[PDB]
Amino acid sequence: QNNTDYPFEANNPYMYHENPMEEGLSMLKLANLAEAALAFEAVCQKEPEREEAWRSLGLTQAENEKDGLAIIALNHARMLDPKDIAVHAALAVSHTNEHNANAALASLRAWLLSQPQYEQLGSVNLQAFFAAPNEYRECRTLLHAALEMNPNDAQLHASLGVLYNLSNNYDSAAANLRRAVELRPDDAQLWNKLGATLANGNRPQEALDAYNRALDINPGYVRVMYNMAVSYSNMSQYDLAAKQLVRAIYMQVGGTTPTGEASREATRSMWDFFRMLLNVMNRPDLVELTYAQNVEPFAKEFGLQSMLLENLY
């Protein structure tokens, strides 16, 4: 759980590449996350002392819904530089998704006190319902104490977003993430986090609105399209949820059918959710049509003759 021995995949083609770090950044510009991760995996085996590589690997695996591997990679990067705040931030998020309270709070704590401007706190005594009741209250006191010093740091609001998500207080996380996107309103990742908090808070209409803002910033954000299929499905709008999934699958693949098996792995969990939805819709004819992984029949069924997704690589 503070483990730094990363289980690299052995059949990694980026092991043969002249420069896999630049290759990983290009895979990021193409928003192609599995490939970026393998490219960063290679930079970490080839050069195990290059801190930015471990960080890039951690953030990428996080972005790709592998919190387990993200934590190992980010623990490793932290071991090379304990003063890296993006590392502490990413750990707090992945620890919160994995339901590891103590490590999440330690990470928020480390995220804060690692910054010169907030380090004064930590020399001051702040001690006085949970799996870590004293660490939580201490962490809550410190982040609010810092918001006094700088009420304009959107990442403090994001950190309080993580803190209150950890305690399933979705309304106070939403309130802080709202403030985070009022500052820093360029950041589609924050809008998506606001969306997911509101969804967990059983406010699905407000989640769609924040998801949609994240898609206006980044119209290729497959994760948000999936998240929106989930919220539309929570409001019983199965047709609108189906339309989001067709979009998300078409966009993830860059086309109508899998251009391989790397495509067929990246869409496994959207076809899985699509299958469930088609069950709820009592349309088992279409559950069968899923395994060919041709979105065309689905595009026709759900009324998407208009696939605006041409910005394809």
Image: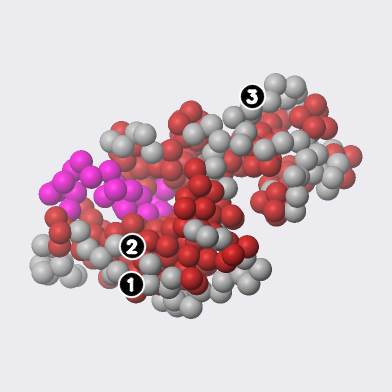
Q: Which mark is residue 89?
A: none
Q: Is residue 158 above or below residue 89?
A: above
Whether residue 101 can be seen here: no
Q: Is residue 144 above or below residue 47?
A: above
Residue position for label 1: 80
Q: Where residue 190 sits in the image (x, y, percent)?
A: 40, 42
Q: Are marks 3 and 2 in contact (CB under 8 Å)?
A: no
User: Outermost residue, top direction?
Assistant: 306
The magenta span reads: 145-171
At x 54% / y 42%, what residue is drawn?
A: 30
Three-letter amino acid code at the position of disc 2: His
At x 43% / y 58%, what residue is drawn?
A: 56
Q: Is residue 153 left or right of residue 305?
A: left
Point out the tag, 3 or 2, that comes first from the N-terminus.
2
Point out the tag, 1 or 3, that comes first from the N-terminus.
1
Q: Nearer the viewer, residue 116 or 104?
A: 116
What SS does tag 1 mark?
Answer: helix
User: Outermost residue, front direction?
Assistant: 18
At x 56% / y 52%, what residue is drawn?
A: 33
Q: Which mark is residue 308?
A: 3
